[PDB]
Image: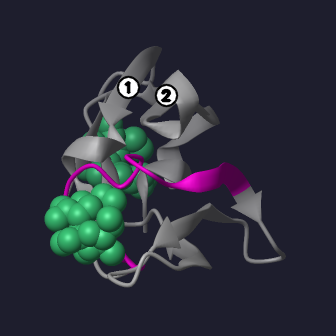
Amino acid sequence: MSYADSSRNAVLTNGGRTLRAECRNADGNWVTSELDLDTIIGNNDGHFQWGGQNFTETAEDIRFHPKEGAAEQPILRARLRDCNGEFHDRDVNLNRIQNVNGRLVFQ
Ligand SMILES: OC[C@H]1O[C@@](CO)(O[C@H]2O[C@H](CO)[C@@H](O)[C@H](O)[C@H]2O)[C@@H](O)[C@@H]1O
Ligand SMILES: OC[C@H]1O[C@@](CO)(O[C@H]2O[C@H](CO)[C@@H](O)[C@H](O)[C@H]2O)[C@@H](O)[C@@H]1O
């Protein structure tokens, strides 16, 4: 279960830092919500880290597939710099992000 189950039209903005969606609220209205991903996802030795910060700082080829695959998962993908300064392609499923009454939150 993620925000995606009750949201639509999810994209990244601000150069891949910002998750922006329309989230169905308590009454079933569709309201705009944005979540700064740099506040909740870090780069830990070239891996995405929930509860980290600033993953975009040197990340390259940031992209987002809101409905990736037959499982339709919200997948963020990026090349991330490891402790040795080498980059590797990485992915993280955004199901730690939830829609709470129309707002995108991190749980
Ligand atoms: O330069 C990236 C490389 O440095 C480390 C050191 O901890 O992470 C730093 O940079 C990240 C953004 O790229 C931040 O998320 C992290 O908080 C900051 O310490 C390594 O973890 C990373 O591989
Ligand atoms: O359906 C929208 C409405 O559902 C709630 C109920 O708590 O959200 C939770 O359940 C959804 C699945 O229907 C998830 O998408 C969502 O992330 C989860 O928080 C309300 O918050 C939301 O307004």
- Tag 1's secondary structure? strand
Q: Quadrant of residue 68?
A: bottom right
Mark 1 surroundings within 10 Å by alpha-carbon count, few (fewer than 14), some (14 through 19), many (20 or more)? some
Say left or right for 96 vs 53.
right
Mark 2 surroundings within 10 Å by alpha-carbon count, few (fewer than 14), some (14 through 19), many (20 or more)? many
Closest to the observer: 4 or 57? 57
| Identity of the residue drawn at 32% across and 33% down | 35
- Tag 2's secondary structure? strand
Q: Which residues are magenta?
A: 46-66
Closest to the observer: 36 or 74? 36
Q: Are marks 2 and 1 in contact (CB under 8 Å)?
A: yes
| Identity of the residue drawn at 72% across and 55% down | 65
Q: Which residue is mark 2?
A: 20
Q: Classify mark 1 as within 8 Å of ligand 2 or not, answering yes or no.
A: no
- The residues bearing labels 2 and 1 have C-alpha atoms spaced at a distance of 4 Å
Residue 43: x %, y % from top left: 32, 68
| Identity of the residue drawn at 37% across and 46% down | 57
Q: Earlier in the sequence, mark 2 or mark 1?
A: 2
| Identity of the residue drawn at 27% across and 49% down | 54
Q: Amino acid at mark 2?
A: Arg
Say left or right for 76 vs 17.
right
Q: Which residue is mark 1?
A: 34
Residue 39 seen anywhere in this rendered image of the structure: yes
Q: Amino acid at mark 1?
A: Glu
